[PDB]
Length: 138
Ligand SMILES: CC(=O)N[C@@H]1[C@@H](O)[C@H](O[C@@H]2O[C@H](CO)[C@H](O)[C@H](O)[C@H]2O)[C@@H](CO)O[C@H]1NC(C)=O
Image (cartoon, rainbow, N blue to C red; front, side):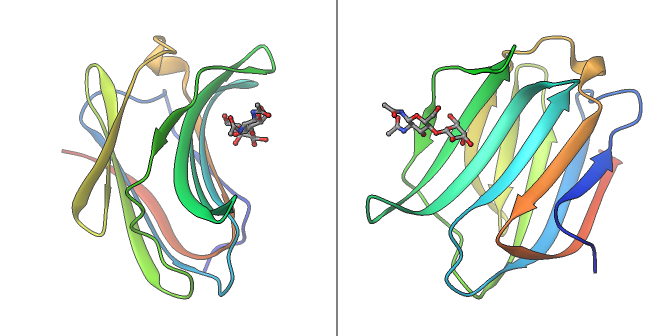
């Protein structure tokens, strides 16, 4: 097991065909999970399952540039459950991050930060027990 928050270095940045796999279990009565793909202080892709935003479960995705959050992209399909093991796979494609949860496609996020090679770390945080975080090329 890994200590949360966990920083996964992405040496030389991300590139198309890189697959990141995250295995963990959601804590009971979780509030949030977050993945933050970083370019220095900037957040290229923030992926943020929220378990109780005004008694709704929602995934919020966004980009933070110069300390400012941009336009949120919201997904109401919510495959995480409190107390239960999950797998998140993030596949870098030429034009977007593609995210699957428990083997099922969830969402795509168009690249707003376009210097992919500068996206050099992934932060994993939130209400989880983290089992594994790794990457491979497909
Ligand atoms: C309903 C709505 O628009 N709520 C937003 C919050 O989502 C937003 O929260 C911040 O969201 C960013 C990602 O976009 C990130 O998850 C931060 O950790 C989180 O604090 C908040 C502040 O940017 O703004 C709310 N908007 C309003 C109108 O208050």
